[PDB]
Amino acid sequence: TPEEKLLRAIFGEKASDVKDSSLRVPNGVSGTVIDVQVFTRDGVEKDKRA
Amino acid sequence: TTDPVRMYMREMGTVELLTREGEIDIAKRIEDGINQVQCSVAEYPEAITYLLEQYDRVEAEEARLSDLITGFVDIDPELAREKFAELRAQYVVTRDTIKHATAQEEILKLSEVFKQFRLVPKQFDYLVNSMRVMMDRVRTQERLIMKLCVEQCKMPKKNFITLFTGNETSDTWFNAAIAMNKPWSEKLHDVSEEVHRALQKLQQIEEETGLTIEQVKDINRRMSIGEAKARRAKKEMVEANLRLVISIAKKYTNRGLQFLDLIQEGNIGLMKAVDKFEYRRGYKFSTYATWWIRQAITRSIADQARTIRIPVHMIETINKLNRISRQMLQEMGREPTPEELAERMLMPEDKIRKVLKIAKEPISMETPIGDDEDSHLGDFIEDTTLELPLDSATTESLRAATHDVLAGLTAREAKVLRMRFGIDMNTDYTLEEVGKQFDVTRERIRQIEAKALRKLRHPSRSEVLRSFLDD
RNA sequence: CGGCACAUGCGAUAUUAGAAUGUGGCGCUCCGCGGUUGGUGAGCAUGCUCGGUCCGUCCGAGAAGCCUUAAAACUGCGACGACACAUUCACCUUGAACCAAGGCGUGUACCG
Image (cartoon, rainbow over the protein chains, first blue to last red):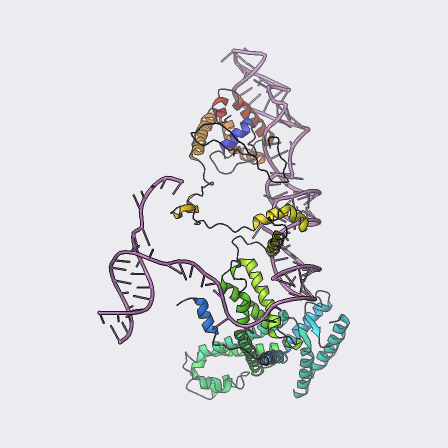
């Protein structure tokens, strides 16, 4: 916008090229993570926990 | 019942089938039609000389052998040179013998050797439509003279036609019938200049094409009757062979396009087949026309049966994937993975994923989710193009805070900093543009800008603006 | 007084067998390269000069250079994309598919 672009200019902070779309717990429960599965398409690098 | 496919069947069910010789008879009527329109061209010298100038454009290396015409009756460039050189000798010996009946057999021989040439339908239909435009201008002048004199001055059409149709060239109808002292001859004296000018424009059109409208009318009514004969023959053959379109279009019905859409695209293909049919090869009409009908129907299904229009070769790739995955599913047994389609086909298996992605038809937005309630799929699709109202609250508070902070600066610093960015005005302005605003040095604006930002980075001004960056 | 036909209401709210080939030109493609006008978040938390000082730091006013201009735009040279036309082979051969049948009402048109 305007003054948001002014502010960015003032403080030099780069608006990042990425967005937090992480998986989150639904609003208002609790409990324990008991089982985690990682399904991965063949031909893609499997990370460390996989 | 309405069921307009059945009304189509009953509208075409009255037309009966053809014998194997009636097709040849209709084709000979088509030959008679094209014969008469080419003989109608054969009397008109301006089309002749027009194609002669286009052939001089061929000989000037601005055209090609495959542009003007194609083929001869026994296509070689030396053959083109010798046949058009004989044509050249013919139209330099033909036209200059008007100095009438001596030249007519020469014009007919020039017409025959013109008819010995197999044209491109572009140039041919161009000559046809140019004759049509010329005829329409002539009829426009005739109806203009009629609407001047006949309806307004109450002149009868029989006394109009009397010395007009029969001469049409000179003032024998015009100037004599004034002198013959008819009761309608007086009413010409307000309109004699415009009627005489239209008559002289009729003479002008005669002088352009060389001959009178007494010949030109018979030329293009001969063309019109020949083309109407050809079009009636082609209507009759299409009405006959609708059955072939139905028998082909029974197969492609479930591929996403409706039944009558398929048979209408097949009828367009059938009309193209009747256009390009040649019986002298000896094949039946069915064997030749079936490929055109299937081509038009397959092209139409690939063209217009999808929401997102995916092209022809892409649909060929999709149909290859479905065919090969139909074959491999009974070979391996489980279903083929695309890793097997890597070595099965010639594609690098990362494109096969996106071809598999593109081939999905979109869901209807009223496709019901379970239990058949009023809940359809449309009531779940969230809007992601709005902004959250909390962001609007941040934008309002940020404009308020920045206005309060820019109030704290000087006049020139605040004015420059508003002018440079998009602050509460129109478009932003750059260095040379602000320099032409204030009649001041470019580098001085950069120095004032750096001093302004240096003034804003210090605390007691940086606090309330650093509050708008969240960690 | 019968028949055929059609319309219309309710049936809760809420929560869950094509294959192959060529040519042509095009670009509302954001893909490499060249040329053209043409900038900005850097030194500069005073690089310089002057003035105030709570000061050796911050306020107020000036001038310059170096360096960030192919960004924004424009036009050409490559890639790609889409489009048109043309050709070769093989096959194919004259009237389809379709669902659903169990409730309660209101009304209209046609014919006898």
